[PDB]
Length: 183
Length: 183
Image (cartoon, rainbow over all chains, first blue to last red; front, side, top):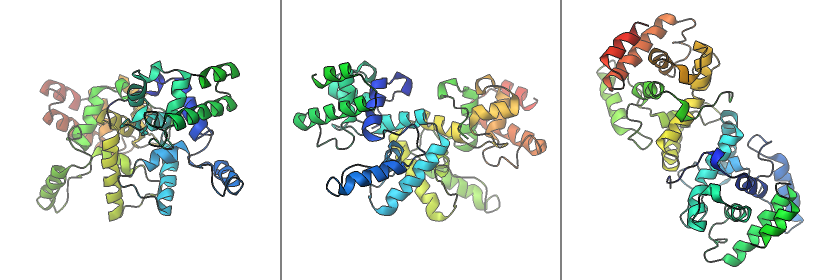
């Protein structure tokens, strides 16, 4: 799971933005933990079926994956929160983004955006289109549930959802959006 | 402490080698933990005053520095060992080396080789000489004890010690060694 690595400079901005708008819209501004995100995850909590948003920042996700074992207790989330905060104090956002983007499991035995660009589109991460970038960003939350190889229904759906988030965040134009959702 | 970052490709091989020969001679071959190193640290333990070598790999050092708090308990060393092993499974050696080399505290408020190349020699890490590289590698174990700014005695000494390790590891030639130790 250390096959393809790619520096952040060789990663399309559509890809980075796709992941940010989908998983941590604030990423560039917080310190490893996102307060508002936890509260916004809490207000869209009981107001959407006592559960919805994630609250977890990209950094917490990176941390989460730095543990050998895979417990999911409370203190675990905390050890990840502390780790994420130290990580934030040690490396800059572009570096954290880079690491996260290269370690993130994206299903079908693919780790990192490069590996995924290959397994899913036979291309290099830097050859990806907006709609291709959007598809990858839709995987992190659940690679097996949204795997385009056997749940293309849910996959395509969550992909167009990523695209809407990007549009709302201003990462893409209405023109580009209409274009992508139809691919 | 996130000021100057420098990709590993812009880092002199004398620098990398200086750190490897001094802190983790096996770095490129182990899996995050170095068994032999712990045993060799143990045999040169009672045979040198019941204590000497370090046993800690570069990866354990990186891990050690990824904790917000700075405890030094037993389980702490273990959490670092597990972390180091997962890190090893996630990123390749050149990447780990890169991260470690950019986070490592080298005294005088300098973090990373770039920051140090400036604070200590007014140069960029890539402009360093063998004897300059050697000096930095001599800092990690104790920046205040070996700080060239006020312990130039101990500093110069441990610097020539790094140079000997490099020579023994074959990273430099006898010619280069004699040259450097006299700078």
